[PDB]
Length: 103
Ligand SMILES: [Zn+2]
Image (cartoon, rainbow, N blue to C red; front, top):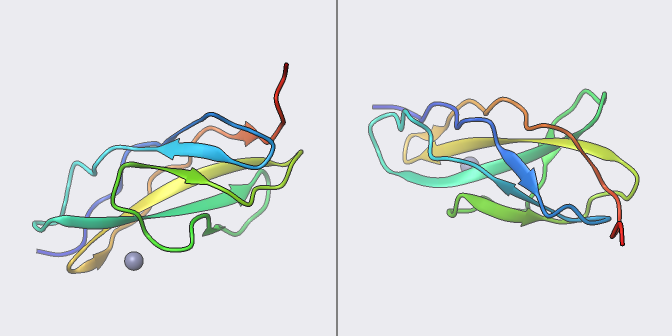
């Protein structure tokens, strides 16, 4: 009974100039104990390092990510944690370009 497995590929939606919604599913493998929260990370397209996209983990399976740079392209990934700790991350989401209202 250890940490969870990866969630499935997250989905990104409701993209504005500096916010987006990231949604995902509960990992198929919870490691044998209840999922207590999720880490969400982001990576600018063709940058190497993944960084925190939210200040602290969330419990719901979606969140509004803020503080994104207009004109930049980002991908997101999600890691689940249980009482035993953090599991490996999901595969990266599709990338999204941060652009303001197209109308
Ligand atoms: Zn954690």
